Amino acid sequence: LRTPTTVSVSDFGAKGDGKTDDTQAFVNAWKKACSSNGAVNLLVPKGNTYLLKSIQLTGPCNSILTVQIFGTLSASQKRSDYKDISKWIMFDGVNNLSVDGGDTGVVDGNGETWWQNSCKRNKAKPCTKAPTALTFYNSKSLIVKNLKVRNAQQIQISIEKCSNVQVSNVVVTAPADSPNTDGIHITNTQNIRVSESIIGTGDDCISIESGSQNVQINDITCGPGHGISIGSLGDDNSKAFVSGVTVDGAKLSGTDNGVRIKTYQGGSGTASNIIFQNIQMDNVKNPIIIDQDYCDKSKCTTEKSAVQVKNVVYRDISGTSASENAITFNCSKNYPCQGIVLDRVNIKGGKATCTNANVVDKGAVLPQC
């Protein structure tokens, strides 16, 4: 094809030994590649390890940028090295961005030291926000592919306020007991497909939050993890909106939940038009769960408002429950779940509990409410 223009971090003094701080080299390389015209590869050379503090790669850019993360990015473990304690690497406002790991690149958050200081893991500790390893924010026409993200400080990959996004052939991994290490976090993002990916992490494999519309999740493996979850929705008495989610082709193994919708008492808004189909459950706790009994304070009041859940289809779901209840519908009394469909569902090893749920059975369904 075209003759490629390449801006390499090598050209800006990045040593690539994993001990020298290469942050400023990345900053300057990003200035060069972002300001250039036309198609530009920003290259992180294969076989090297680049220690990075927090870094913000800000657009919009004159270039059509392909960031070739072929080597390894290694996070500082010093809390003072993070401008925003919630962010390690953040792409901000970059349109027509493609991030390609070439099946060799690794984004390593070095999260263990953050995890042991987490309050979920040491209750003599205060609960603190830890950095998201890789954030894409305010991007249109985004592509993320062929990349591995491991051991994030907290959230591994977050896609926030994005539009027209394709994530394909990524690997996200962290220990099963690592706290709050969401695999792929999707929030206020519309028209996104995540396909052909593998997530085994310490929290939600995929979490879909408010503002999300037209989300496609195809051919993913999840385990360890907390499953594929819409929510949390309506926390802090927020108005939530989620519409048009399809998970089609997934294998969940040993996860704390299978396919989950979770909303908070006091919330408002709606979560609608959701389809979970062609799902294999291998020893999964809470294979199917909608749970609206959540509150964000230590002493919950009687619920005045709830997120309304409507048009949820569970289709061609098969496998084995590790929970007493394979199917759990705990929905709001004042806003009951509506248009819940169970179509060719066969989960053995568990029973079904259904409260304030209008369910419809289509074909062979086991277990039944």
Image (cartoon, rainbow, N blue to C red):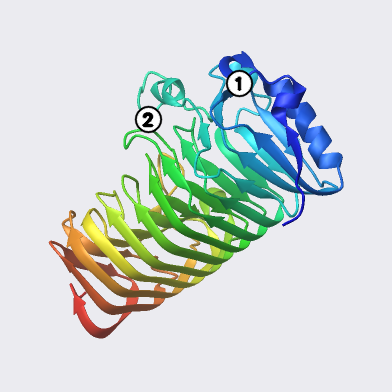
Closer to us: 71 or 290: 71
Point out residue 137 in the picture as x, y percentages from the top left corner: 68, 47
Q: Which residue is depicted at the point 57% across and 37% down?
A: 70
Closer to us: 303 or 111: 111
Q: Which residue is mark 2?
A: 120
Which marked residue is nearer to the observer: mark 2 or mark 1? Answer: 1
The amino acid at mark 2 is Lys
Residue extending furthest toward the top: 20
Q: CA distance from mark 2 to mark 1?
A: 34 Å
327 with respect to 216 (left or right): left
Point out residue 258 in the picture as x, y percentages from the top left corner: 31, 58
Q: Secondary structure at mark 1?
A: loop
Residue 59 seen in render: yes
Point out residue 113 in the picture as x, y percentages from the top left corner: 44, 20
Q: Quadrant of residue 276?
A: bottom left
Q: Which residue is mark 1?
A: 16
The amino acid at mark 1 is Gly
Q: Quadrant of residue 318?
A: bottom left
Q: Which quadrant is the N terminus positioned in? A: bottom right
Q: Is residue 84 above or below residue 90?
A: above
Closer to us: 279 or 338: 279
